[PDB]
Length: 125
Ligand SMILES: *C(=O)/C=C\c1ccc(O)cc1
Image (cartoon, rainbow, N blue to C red; front, side, top):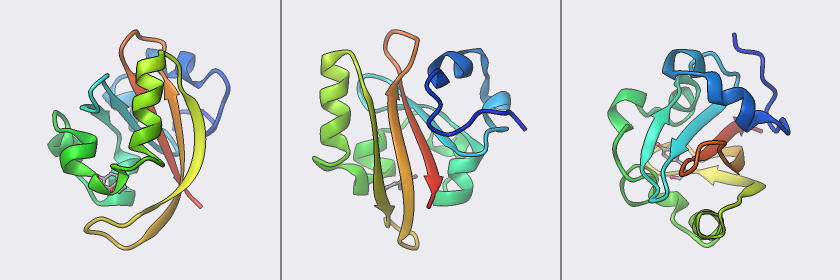
């Protein structure tokens, strides 16, 4: 397993060295999006939670297609502001409930080290 704690201050630095293979070792969900909400990476842990297939969601809009239950001021609203500002680091509780059992999780959004990429870290609570 890759030893990285959810909410770690330097998490964007640590994860810059990973690949899809290495990301699959994390204890929590991790989604990498571009400036437009498109999925660039999708680890095995978020798949265990949402039931999605990582390899099948890659390339689709996170907010439009895959997870419309996030299209909201509380989530998407926060993402867009972050993207436009060029900085993003917020943590909140959300309920995943689209075509799945209503699941309470902890969501950590943070801008990555790379120019135009954003992290979505998730964990059951
Ligand atoms: C609501 O849709 C919230 C979360 C979520 C995340 C990923 C996937 O694939 C579905 C739903």
